[PDB]
Image (tube, coloured by chain):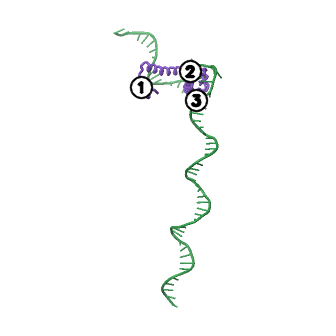
Chain colours: A purple, B green
Amino acid sequence: ELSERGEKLPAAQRRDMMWICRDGDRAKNHLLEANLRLVVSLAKRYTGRGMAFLDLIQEGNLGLIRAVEKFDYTKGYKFSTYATWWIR
DNA sequence: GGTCAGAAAATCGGTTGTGGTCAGCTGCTGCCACCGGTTAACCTCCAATTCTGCTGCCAGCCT
């Protein structure tokens, strides 16, 4: 929203701004790769009726991505209790 | 002890007249079918035989 209409060159400030932008996505990817086992453990109980196993796991992956989008830390709860709703 | 206007038939066709009649939407109004988002104690790794060709493998003369 700033570079849409305004141009500035602080070199160190722009470098650390891009550093924040990169490492936020690094953090998000690390969180998803941490909770993949939760996704698999939830999806292992729906097998045998209708769909395959890995389709269920990838749908749980989409639900986990949405839960990471919707997560809030100010209420102060364990992440798995919030993410189980979106995965299911 | 014969010719000419009128009357009386269907006949082909235009008027017409209204009497419904059916649909063609047209709101419209309620409703109902369908799609999307959301839920905050915790609990984080699966259910037989026959034949031909190919590749992987190990000793072993040769340099």
Same chain assignment for discs 2 and 3: yes
Determine which residue is flagged by label 2.
A35
A19 relative position to B9: left or right: left
Mark 1 crowdedness (10 Å alpha carbons): few <14, some 14-19, many ≥20: few
Asked if residue A85 is positioned above or below residue B30 in the image, the reply reads: above
- Mark on residue A80? none
- Mark on residue A7? 1
**B41 or A62, which lies in front?**
B41
Q: Position of residue B10 (x, y in %)?
A: 55, 73
Determine which residue is flagged by label 3.
A51
Mark 2 crowdedness (10 Å alpha carbons): few <14, some 14-19, many ≥20: some
Dot 1 lies on which element? loop
**A15 or A48, which lies in front?**
A15
Q: Nearer the viewer, mark 1 or mark 2?
A: 1
Q: Position of residue A48 (x, y in %)?
A: 60, 28
Tags 2 and 3 touching, CB below 8 Å: no
Q: Is residue A72 visible?
A: yes
> Which quarter of the figure has residue B30?
top right
Label 1 marks a residue whose chain is A
| Of the image marks 2 and 3, the number of the one nearer the N terminus | 2
| Of the image marks 3 and 1, the number of the one nearer the N terminus | 1
> Which quarter of the figure has residue B34?
top right
| Of the image marks 1 and 2, the number of the one nearer the N terminus | 1
